[PDB]
Amino acid sequence: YAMDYPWKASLPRIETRLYLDQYGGSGDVWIGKVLHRMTLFCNDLYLKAAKADFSNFQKECRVELNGLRRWYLRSNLEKFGGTDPQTTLMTSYFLASANIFEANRAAERLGWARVALLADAVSSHFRRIGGPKNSTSNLEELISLVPFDDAYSGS
Amino acid sequence: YAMDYPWKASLPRIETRLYLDQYGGSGDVWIGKVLHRMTLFCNDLYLKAAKADFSNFQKECRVELNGLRRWYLRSNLEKFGGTDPQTTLMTSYFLASANIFEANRAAERLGWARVALLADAVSSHFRRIGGPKNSTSNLEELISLVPFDDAYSGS
């Protein structure tokens, strides 16, 4: 994994799932003059911390895409663009949630993935008419499909 | 003044101006059993006190007038409006400045003026077209004339 995925392109979440699938724990032994183990270093407990918090993170985020689904399919924006909405829906939430993965900054997390899906289905719409020379529908009103909050939606 | 200006028609700045003409200071003399004075509140420096409080009130009454009159021109609004827009600006800003007379509430004083132009001048526009039936544009766009404060704008 390290030779073909450099630091420059690795998401900070993909291998953290894969690191569970590669880690033995305290069933792994160092040799020396005499073989030995290290329990401040390797336990069956660091996994128990990790298979607790990452597992409920995997739990608590897949109900969010379940909640993020219908908004895309109700705000009249899913109609045009790609061949199908669902593969663009799951792609745009992956890179928007593999980076930020803690339960206190969801408002930044899901608000990222919304305006992720806003700017590309309209990027599709401009080439399908050939640029902004022959577009007539007003485009600064699509920005209101994100709900109005005071602390965010001003600027 | 007190026989034709009820409490429902008495404004807190046109009142103060109309008492300085009948204010005496220490020149007002009281009659008891003996012709006698009372130096404390019947006092001549009090007349100079409020008049020192009243000039510096009016000094911002000219510069917010000059400040607003350059904004109303460039905003392309004199297309609409009454045939005398300067006095229409006068009758709108005064109706705020006679109400709020404290200094550091200028943002309340400017906003009450700047909304009540573009909220009134549109009502002239509908008297020609018949209502909202025969409209030809999006009337929602007319807060572009309003300055952007990053806290105050969106709500």
Image: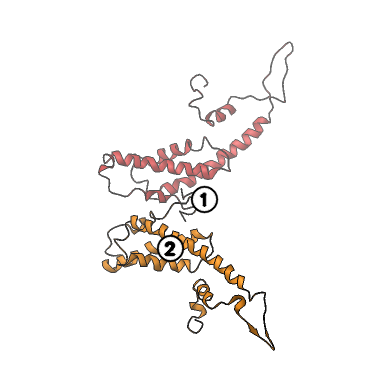
Chain colours: A red, B orange
Q: Please, is residue A37 above or below residue B4 in the view?
A: above
Total count of labels: 2
Could you tell me residue B34's position as x and y percent?
A: 69, 87
The Cα atoms of the two marked residues, 1 and 2, are separated by 25 Å
Say which of marks 1 and 2 sits in front: 2
Q: Chain of mark 1?
A: A
Q: Which mark is residue A151?
A: 1
Name the residue located 37 percent from the left edge and 51 percent from the top edge. A141
Please name the amino acid that badge 1 sits on.
Answer: Ala
Q: Please, is residue B29 above or below residue B48 in the view?
A: below
Q: Which mark is residue B113?
A: 2
Give A119 or B65, whichever is nearer the viewer: B65
Q: Is label 1 on the same chain as label 2? A: no
Left or right of residue B145: residue B98: right
Q: Which mark is residue B21?
A: none
Which residue sits furthest bottom? B33
Please name the amino acid that badge 2 sits on.
Answer: Ala
Could you tell me residue A7's position as x and y percent?
A: 51, 24
Q: Residues within 10 Å of mark 2 (few under 14, many from 20)?
A: many
Residue B94 in view:
yes
Q: Residues within 10 Å of mark 1 (few under 14, many from 20)?
A: few
Q: Please, is residue B30 above or below residue A23 in the view?
A: below
Q: Chain of mark 2?
A: B
Give A86 or B18, whichever is nearer the viewer: B18
Name the residue located 34 percent from the left edge and 65 percent from the top edge. B85
Left or right of residue B115: residue B29: right
